[PDB]
Image (spheres, rainbow, N blue to C red):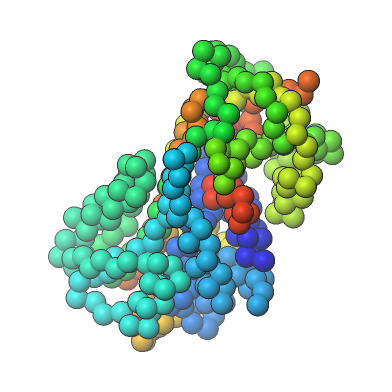
């Protein structure tokens, strides 16, 4: 199952991300999968086999690219209550020729469009053009995706994925009920925060065992939901993080294993913005040939010689009384019950029909 593969890669990412100093974590695993999927399509031999393993695409069954193409289709839908959109794009050096085969394949499986830019003579201005396209696909929430240092006059390829979601809560919060309260990042310390509050019935589950609770907060239309995992104890997050695997997430957070239940939901207004340099991270995870001289990306060009210089990700979420807005992008460069979220919690945004986790995060502090 592909949904499962993507969710496993999501946890493999999370364990790496835990090592940086940043308190909050927020990223789109699907955006990253999509960008690396476009790289895989042009990879060969061992270069390809390492990518497949990192993405868990070697564990999907029946061609994976076809299954991903079906997913991409589902992720482009707007109603009156929400917008979800995803796009893939290839920016190549103007004078540089890709295999028609490779172009047809990314067009077909990843809906990728192609734009030619002048990296050779204008690498800085090319950088800024890619960064603006990304703004343009993210309601301007992802700015400066690719910082200086990453594009040069020898750059021949930047593959980019952008994903954007904005949706209304099915049951909105009343701004009149929002109040300043303390948020405790640790047992013995606090920061002020605007706490939204409502009493309503939601699918709920108590996970007595990791000493946590789970809540589903639907978006209007119920195509998407935000799932939140709240440790029972102020300091219990570290255990929950150790025990939450893809298999456990799938069990605990399915409708099947939750129940409609009335909850004083207290959820803070919050905003998270984070950046990731993914090169060394993916290297650790198993993707080595692609970043060095062994690289085989001859499926892109017809011969070896292309190597990836970087992989960058940036992500944004904001939660308000009306709903939530979430965005991310990835660049690859080549050459009765209470649920009170007043201490750290995990959250994610899921597309319910496909069971896909589009965005995943940890809120540790305002």
**Residue 186 place in picture, x, y as percent:** 65, 24
Q: Is residue 17 left or right of residue 111?
A: right
Residue 62 position by quadrant? bottom right
**Residue 39 place in picture, x, y as percent:** 44, 71
Determine the residue positioned at 60% across, 38% down: 218
Q: Is residue 127 left or right of residue 9?
A: left
Of 59 and 67, nearer the camera is: 67
Residue 363 position by quadrant? top right
Determine the residue positioned at 51% across, 58% down: 74
Determine the residue positioned at 73% across, 47% down: 254
- Whether residue 117 is visible here, answered yes or no, is yes
* Total marks placed: 0
Asked if 208 appears above or below 180 in the picture, the reply is below
Determine the residue positioned at 54% across, 54% down: 29
**Residue 99 place in picture, x, y as percent:** 33, 83
Q: Quadrant of the N terminus?
A: bottom right
**Residue 38 place in picture, x, y as percent:** 44, 69
> Residue lying furthest left in this view?
121
Q: Is residue 278 left or right of residue 55?
A: left
> Residue lying furthest right in this view?
209
Of 22 and 79, nearer the camera is: 79
């Amino acid at each position: 199952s592909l949904s499962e593969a993507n969710t496993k890669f999501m946890f493999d990412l999370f364990q790496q991300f835990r090592k940086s100093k940043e308190n909050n974590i927020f990223y789109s695993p699907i955006s990253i999968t999509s960008a690396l999927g476009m790289v895989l399509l042009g990879a060969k031999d061992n270069t390809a086999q390492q990518i497949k393993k990192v993405l868990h695409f070697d564990q999907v069954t029946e061609n994976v690219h076809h299954q991903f193409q079906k997913l991409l289709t589902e992720f482009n839908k707007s109603t009156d209550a929400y917008e979800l959109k995803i796009a893939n794009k290839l920016f190549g050096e103007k004078t540089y020729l890709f295999l028609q085969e490779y172009l047809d394949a990314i067009k077909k499986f990843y809906q990728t469009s192609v734009e030619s830019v002048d990296f050779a003579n204008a690498p800085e201005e090319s950088r800024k053009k890619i960064n603006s396209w990304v703004e343009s696909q993210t309601n301007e929430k992802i700015k400066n995706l690719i910082p200086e240092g990453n594009i040069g006059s020898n750059t021949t390829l930047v593959l980019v994925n952008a994903i954007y979601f904005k949706g209304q809560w099915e049951k909105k919060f009343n701004k009149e009920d929002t109040k300043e309260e303390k948020f405790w990042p640790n047992k013995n310390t606090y920061k002020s925060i605007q706490m939204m509050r409502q009493y309503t019935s939601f699918h709920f589950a108590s996970l007595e065992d990791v000493q946590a609770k789970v809540l589903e907060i639907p978006y209007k239309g119920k195509d998407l939901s935000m799932i939140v995992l709240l440790p029972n104890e102020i300091d219990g997050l570290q255990k929950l993080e150790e025990k939450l695997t893809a298999e456990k997430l799938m069990e605990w957070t399915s409708l099947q294993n939750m129940r409609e239940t009335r909850v004083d939901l207290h959820l803070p207004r919050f905003k998270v913005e984070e950046s990731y340099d993914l090169k060394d991270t993916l290297r650790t995870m198993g993707m080595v040939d692609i970043f060095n001289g062994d690289a085989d990306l001859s499926g892109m060009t017809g011969s070896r010689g292309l190597v990836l210089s970087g992989v960058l990700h940036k992500a944004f979420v904001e939660v308000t009384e009306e709903g939530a807005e979430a965005a991310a992008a990835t660049a690859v460069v080549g050459f009765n019950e209470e649920f009170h979220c007043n201490h750290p919690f995990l959250f994610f945004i899921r597309q319910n029909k496909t069971n896909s986790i589009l965005f995943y995060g940890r809120f540790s502090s305002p």
